[PDB]
Amino acid sequence: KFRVRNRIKRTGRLRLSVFRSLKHIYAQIIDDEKGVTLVSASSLALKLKGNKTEVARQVGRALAEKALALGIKQVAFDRGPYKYHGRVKALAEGAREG
Amino acid sequence: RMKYRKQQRGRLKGATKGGDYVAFGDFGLVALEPAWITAQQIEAARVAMVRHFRRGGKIFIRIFPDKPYTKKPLEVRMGKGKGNVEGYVAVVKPGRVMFEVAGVTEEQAMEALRIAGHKLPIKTKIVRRDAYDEAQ
Amino acid sequence: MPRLKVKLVKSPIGYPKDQKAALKALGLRRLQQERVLEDTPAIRGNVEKVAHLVRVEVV
Amino acid sequence: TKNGRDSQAKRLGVKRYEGQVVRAGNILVRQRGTRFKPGKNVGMGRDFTLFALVDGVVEFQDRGRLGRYVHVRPLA
Amino acid sequence: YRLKAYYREGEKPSALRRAGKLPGVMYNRHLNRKVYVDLVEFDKVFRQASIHHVIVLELPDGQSLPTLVRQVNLDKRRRRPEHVDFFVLSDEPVEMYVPLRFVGTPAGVRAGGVLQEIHRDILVKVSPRNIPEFIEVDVSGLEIGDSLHASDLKLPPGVELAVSPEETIAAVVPPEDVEKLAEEAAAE
RNA sequence: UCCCCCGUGCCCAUAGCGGCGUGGAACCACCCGUUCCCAUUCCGAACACGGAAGUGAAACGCGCCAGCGCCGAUGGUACUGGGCGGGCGACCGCCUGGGAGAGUAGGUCGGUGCGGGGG
RNA sequence: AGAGCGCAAGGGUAGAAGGGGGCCUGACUGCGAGGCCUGCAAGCCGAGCAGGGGCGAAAGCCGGGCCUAGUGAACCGGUGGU
RNA sequence: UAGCUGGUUCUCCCCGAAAUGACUUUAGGGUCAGCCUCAGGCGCUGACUGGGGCCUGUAGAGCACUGAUAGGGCUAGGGGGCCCACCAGCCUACCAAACCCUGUCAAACUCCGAAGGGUCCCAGGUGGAGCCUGGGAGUGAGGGCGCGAGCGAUAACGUCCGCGUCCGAGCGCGGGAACAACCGAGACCGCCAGCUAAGGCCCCCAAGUCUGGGCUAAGUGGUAAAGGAUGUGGCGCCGCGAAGACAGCCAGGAGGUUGGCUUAGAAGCAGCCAUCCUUUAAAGAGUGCGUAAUAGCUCACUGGUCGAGUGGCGCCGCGCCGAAAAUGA
Ligand SMILES: [Mg+2]
Ligand SMILES: [Mg+2]
Ligand SMILES: [Mg+2]
Ligand SMILES: [Mg+2]
Ligand SMILES: [Mg+2]
Ligand SMILES: [Mg+2]
Ligand SMILES: [Mg+2]
Ligand SMILES: [Mg+2]
Ligand SMILES: [Mg+2]
Ligand SMILES: [Mg+2]
Ligand SMILES: [Mg+2]
Ligand SMILES: [Mg+2]
Ligand SMILES: [Mg+2]
Ligand SMILES: [Mg+2]
Ligand SMILES: [Mg+2]
Ligand SMILES: [Mg+2]
Ligand SMILES: [Mg+2]
Ligand SMILES: [Mg+2]
Ligand SMILES: [Mg+2]
């Protein structure tokens, strides 16, 4: 399953591969047509505490700082076979809130 | 048989795929010229083959007719021919192996295949066996 | 690219259009005509396709 | 009999070829279904028509499982 | 057996045949060389030799290679060999079609039957040293309508059937004279 | 600089069917529970949520083997731009340039980008 | 992928175009770069723009049905508006 | 009125077609397009060619889909038999789905797939090339031939499409006896010049009764097949041979056995099967003719005679039979 993924691929640039673990929640700004990650704010495998949801909000804010630094803004999010509602929600939620 | 009504004429190019090797039996019968062999020509050779040596061994007919032979009832040009008159035929090209006997002597086969040669339109040859297969 | 003497000997009458156009690109008029051209890759290909009509020479 | 019949020619297939310059909108290739997929700067319509979205050159890219893609590399 | 071979290089393939030489090539897991035998020689040699026994090729290099024809391109339009391969052996085991001498008087022939014979040879994994001229076939208890399979073969030591363990070997079919002709002509 | 992992793109089966073995502290999945977000036309099987124990069986990652799938030269043919010849015809042959399919030897239980965690 | 994709057949397709539920009406008006096809006429595709509106968090999709058949120049007249 | 037929008058000079497509109460007529020619513009863009990229599904081949398909194995089902209704089990030189193997066929089947062609870019390419605008036509029955397909009957100077060519319009010239389109060759005119092309080089008839090496004795040549035959020549293979070969010749060619069964009668010699031993230098559980059936003649075998070769097989070339028509060959 990855229909959505392919939809965004042809869309444009600066994908946001939000692969989450059962407890972790990684996030990478991969740009296709070359395959290169930019802002890769990891979660549990980075520094943050232990609270998947609230941890997601912050790790999202982590992308914002690093991203706004490199002059990026295209919010080409990547659901990555995940329903927008819980953890993945806070991801783009916090990242776009700033 | 079974498939559907009519088929094209088509030409008979090189004696390529129309040719093989003694795949069964001891002796065999090979065509020297191209031609469509009729269902009757087959039955003619077959019956004459077994009728020669009574209670004979086993006769293998490798070829097989399936091409509808078209023909018009002595008139003119309305639509395609009804065909089927002579029945069917097989794309026999030089080198091919029509008949081949087995479990029998050499004289019976030598005569029977010779006889079954006249039953066929094409000038033919009779091959023994050799050992030409495909191995090591 | 050495010189290439090419003499016409076989009348193009009865041969396909392309071949005729070939001898035009080579500039061949009447029979038994002389024509010294370079040995360039293209010029070769044309004289080749009409080799049965003309006798090539290496000068 | 009752056979003499045939819809006239639709004249499909590859229209544009690789190494060809093109304007903006040129129907690169007409097709029956998905004998060819879109690609970089290449859109399609209902009849599965392939056409440029930008200006550049046509290029073909076979990819086995995925299929045969066609795109136009922009330049000026 | 022996056979006088030679090295090829640029001799025209077709024009070669017209002279009296049969084109061919030897090779193995490491080798590869354009060769060519003689028609008349190869003929009589390969007649008995066929593709079961080994034949060493004496190259002008004095090299005696234990080769065996891995394949032959039979020419259509009146049979005749066009090309020939030559797989060179060493010591590693190698598959190949070994002969089969069916021996015995099957019960089928007694009641008036037909000598059916499927695999007149069988491919089998085997060491180069092993060169069985043939394998005994105990065909005798075979009555009409019966058959013999590969799962019932007698295998000599150091060998295995490099085939499906169920394949057929031979059978016993009936005649087909008057009873069939008379019956079939009306029943069709 | 180098090795094992998590993500994710490239080559599009030499990367798979399979049989065996390895890995758990770290990563990953399974596992506990169903109050809250949310949900199964019925089920917390999945989708979702708050997370300790246990496991590494499942699944995935890494290696080994060629029984199947897969890739498969070399040599020689079949056919054929162009030139030419023979038959009454069905057709056949020669010079030049080109040249598969099949089959045989053989090859394969993957290679490779960038970002990130650990030594 | 040998099914399904309303109906013929073909090309296509489960990395959806196929089956289900939610909301809902782009089965819009005013346009149209540049094209395929083409003797003429006709047919066919269409980015992007404006107004305005549907679904979605959003990137975005929607100018009717996976697609190629389901049709008729002109004239003469009908009905409603401008 | 005549979309029909017939006629259409002086000369020289350049170029020079069509007999296709689309629609037509249209088919032997038209309209637009295509092909011809002028006039004015544009100037390496033309035909053809070298190199590079891309597209495609034929020849061929193949059996991975769709179908056909010969033989075997395995095997669900149907039929018959052993057997009994408590309804299974077993056989089944039977019909036979599915699966495997052996082996094949296909325009509307394709795992595979050339030569080639189409197109864009780069370069040669100055030609009665090409592009643009406008005046003017005619053409819209085409035919052979070669190649690839359909229809036909793998018939037609047949027909209908494609690629190319010639006649058309080059029934001007040479060859082919004569002959629009087969081979040569593209005629501005003149010459009592020379070389050549095809095809020819004894005479009618221009040129070698030329040279070397073979094949054929049928007038093949001077052109017809399946099939048939110690016609003649050349290459390769195997058997017998001076320890005595092939043919003919001299004798024998025997017993059980009148081989078993069978049969009005088979006795090696109407029909089916089995499928030895003795003597010997040799005679086979027996080849042909005969006979109601035996008797009798014969071969292989052995020996002697005899004395140098002999038989079979395959392949290459030329030739023979097969071969009967109408005014004169
Ligand atoms: Mg015959
Ligand atoms: Mg363990
Ligand atoms: Mg191949
Ligand atoms: Mg389908
Ligand atoms: Mg859907
Ligand atoms: Mg739908
Ligand atoms: Mg138009
Ligand atoms: Mg339409
Ligand atoms: Mg707008
Ligand atoms: Mg009117
Ligand atoms: Mg007309
Ligand atoms: Mg006109
Ligand atoms: Mg074919
Ligand atoms: Mg090209
Ligand atoms: Mg013509
Ligand atoms: Mg002309
Ligand atoms: Mg003439
Ligand atoms: Mg001459
Ligand atoms: Mg005669």
Image (cartoon, coloured by chain):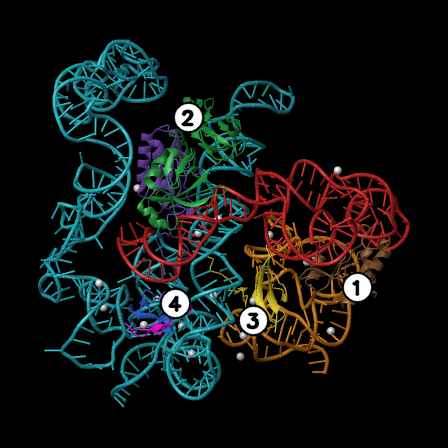
Chain colours: A brown, B purple, C blue, D yellow, E green, F red, G orange, H cyan
Task: Write the start and end of the magenta stretch as one range.
Answer: C26-48
Badge 2: chain ID: E
Asked if residue A41 is among those painted magenta in the image, a careful observer would answer: no
Determine if the C-beta at disc 1 is less than 8 A from ligand 9: no
Badge 1: chain ID: A
Q: Is residue F95 above or below residue B119?
A: below
In the picture of the structure, the residue carrying the numbered disc 3 is D21
Q: Is residue E2 left or right of residue A5?
A: left
Marks 3 and 4: which is nearer the front?
A: 4
Marks 3 and 1: which is nearer the front?
A: 1
Mark 1 near mark 4, Cβ–Cβ under 8 Å?
A: no
| Residue found at x 75% / y 66% | A74
- Please tell me whether mark 4 sits on a helix, a strand or a loop: helix
Quick check: can you spot residue B4? no
Please tell me the numbered disc located at residue C44.
4
Mark 2 near mark 3, Cβ–Cβ under 8 Å?
A: no
In the picture of the structure, the residue carrying the numbered disc 1 is A66
Residue type, label 3: Val
Residue type, label 4: Arg
What x and y, as percent, mark residue A64?
A: 81, 64
Please tell me the numbered disc located at residue E113.
2
- Count residues near mark 3 (Cα–Cα under 10 Å), then give few for <14, some for 14-19, many for 20+: few
- Please tell me whether mark 2 sits on a helix, a strand or a loop: loop
Marks 2 and 1: which is nearer the front?
A: 1
What x and y, as percent, mark residue E154?
A: 50, 25
Q: Is residue E124 left or right of residue A72?
A: left
Badge 3: chain ID: D
Please tell me the numbered disc located at residue E91.
none
Quadrant position of residue C33: bottom left
Q: Are marks 2 and 1 on the same chain?
A: no
Measure the alpha-carbon separation of dots 1 and 4.
64 Å
